[PDB]
Length: 216
Image (cartoon, rainbow, N blue to C red; front, side, top):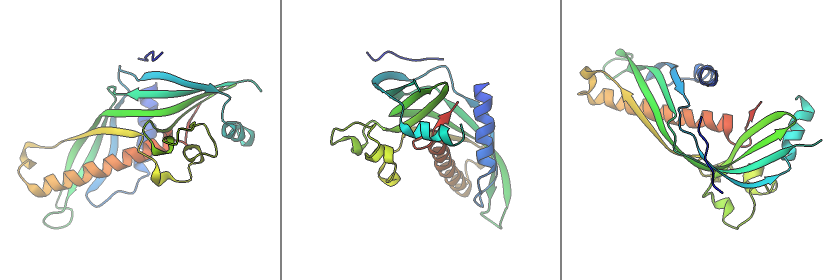
């Protein structure tokens, strides 16, 4: 019973991600970060229902502070969809001098691979969405439920020992003709690509990964 899903949101994600970026301290090699475009795409995840339970008490606890009869789905989610983020960056070349040059440059984050247990909780009628952990996370080996609150995943006491939710991700960069020869530029671009990779994964973890969640 592994029955699919396919599908303003894009603009909301764009402005939020933009805020995140504008609130990030930048290395010497990048002057400016901005989201040129965000696109969730046309292709969605393969969804398998794993279990269905009462919502986690942590949700109720959250509501009781600021924000009965309700429901929660434990889902296995397998994503190899067509999400695309296009980010504008001002690459700073420091090879000769400091701030020798600035190249407007555009990076493309694409081809996101994901295979993870998430949860979707209806609590009348706020909606909670959170990615718990990757499918092949070692904390699932001893063959016990994820929804165990005293268990490793939900307790979130050892974030280091968690497998990354994002399995794969592709970053490309568009630079000028003129710079494809110079190794210094290529190196700076590499550094920027790595930095943006870690930044984006960080953002996703802070927005979607348990104990964080998307609240509606």
